[PDB]
Length: 197
Length: 186
Image 1 (cartoon, helix red, strand yellow):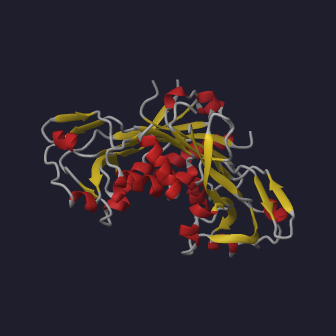
Image 2 (cartoon, rainbow over the protein chains, first blue to last red):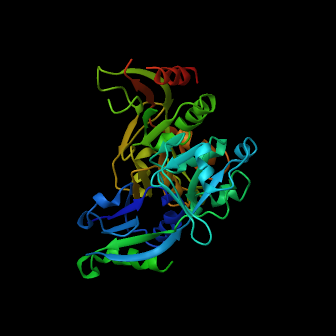
Image 3 (cartoon, chains in turn cyan, yellow):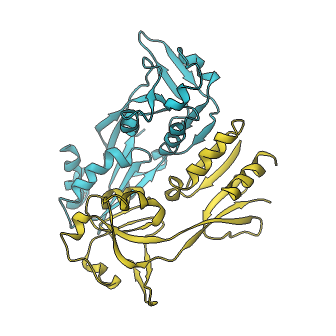
């Protein structure tokens, strides 16, 4: 066509998928990108998109890992200064929790194999993550959020890591497409530029 | 729990500071929020209601302007008229895939060209605009941050979109009414 059709995860687009595209379009001023942000990539099929970025497997298509994220628990310094903070991950029931898609079910694990699972009704639940980060900045509860999204917020004192020995199983970002012999030349150069990262 | 829908792009700068203040005043209220009419208790929307079932309250307004980076304007001849936007690079994000710019003297221009970068969101389109990759059309609220500190410059200072309004839709309980009273007062 006269464009390439991308799919991209909802929350991690701005920080991990943009420097790659903002350097790609700067290398090819003749290519047009159309980006779409999705919540459930399980309802997508591959022939309607050139390449598909996604967190998780595909349940056919090429599946390559470009990066990964690990999820941390954070709250505002205003929030920790207002209550005695939890020392064991099961004390999360006695706190305000801010959940966001796709992390509505917190699965945490410490050292030597203890797993805690939290499936609650948080004080503020949403389908995006950048918006519950805005909630924990004011200090209205605790949030589990990927490393890449808050790495600047936490590094300034705007948010602090709590329960530092409790982490989440990492999730990896996968890029999907059909066999290269079935896609135009414009799609190939984008694919290999991503792998060049 | 109150169930609320909001437009994606305007949520960061408008819905949140008001939403965050409400839960800060009502800890007993749980809020579920999805960013994009009976499966919702309160719906924030661009444009007037399309259903006599709802009662709307205009709570704000938004006007869009043309922006680029100083790296872009100092590397290209900045255009003089909105018709010159074809000889330039354009970045477009929903719901502004087409630009209906008007001038002070009344001239109206429509641009429906395919941009170098197109997305269903605007935060990601501005991200490409901060890299000096073309000219954008973005709401004033979403860019007072970057304009007022040299990240983005304004292009064609008298060409702009015309104000779309922000309406609050609801169905004329307890918790849902106070939040309605809260936003009116905000």
